[PDB]
Image (cartoon, rainbow over all chains, first blue to last red; front, side):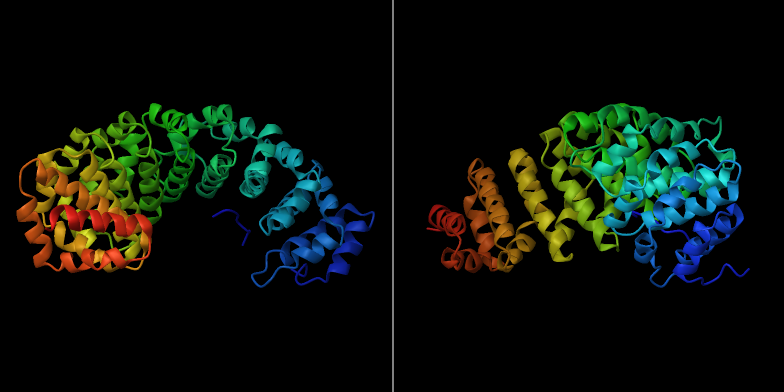
Length: 7
Length: 427
């Protein structure tokens, strides 16, 4: 949940 | 749509043309590449020297689509390794994204929220650098609405998430006044009815409560404890987990702070938290119990009147080792602050057998922990003249062998405790 990529 | 599957050198070609449209097209190709599930060529994109170009597209207000495509593109690079993030930051993206927060196009500022989220997520330094560039005002502004329901579902999810990252990490913790500034909105979010806003709100709070008392106190003082307790009883594990952590943190502070949690009704959820099927909930609930049994006798008493001792006994008797370890502690803590009655009570709940069985675990730490506890228990039994009936007990369930074989355990304080115990109560 640190970081999120899109799609 | 044939902006699918371009080669990097193609993307470069386009972004370098002097044709705003050609560039828009290539940037979309760039985003698409970077959006693929199998190893998006982030590195070569970086290596191609593209980041600054994307960064400057953020500033192109006439051409919203490019703003968006480049936003998204950087968002995805910024989501990779620290080093990848570092590259986004080194490009000057931060003030650029902050500027985009106020863009009239929701889908664009959302992208900006998202990216700032990833940058702040890298770790305390980037986080505080986002903060210095003044991200917090404009973020909060997007949440300045009479009713949070009127915002789009995933828009609010992103802001809640980004906000939580601005509360995340610990060396150093976020700036006090940045926290003061965020708290009220966080509180308002902790009350919204989206499971995902609630999970992240809970994390945010859990991060902010993971420090010294003054920090805990900031939180506790906004009166979120009732609301944390309620969430603690939720059906969604993504919500229980971070709520339970918050509570666990809070009870590491002052006893006054601990009591807020008790008053909130926290203890009532424990019968089920201490039996929860998810291993980690149990560990974390047990740990939490250990910090309550570390408090005053009237706090120990409240644990008693909620009938949590059987639950501790249960947890001591069978859980995965890591939980049993916390139970061990919870008991020792109990047996430290507890009144004579209270220590007696523990034994009547059948704490002696399952405690003893743990003496044959090959973890050096827990054994000391248990023995302190036996020590402690005999102590209340001395004050009653019952060291006998208790010795007998410990014999009949094979505890005596286990301790008497423990003088030949290597560790120093270990063989001395057993030594002491043997000498003192067993001849």
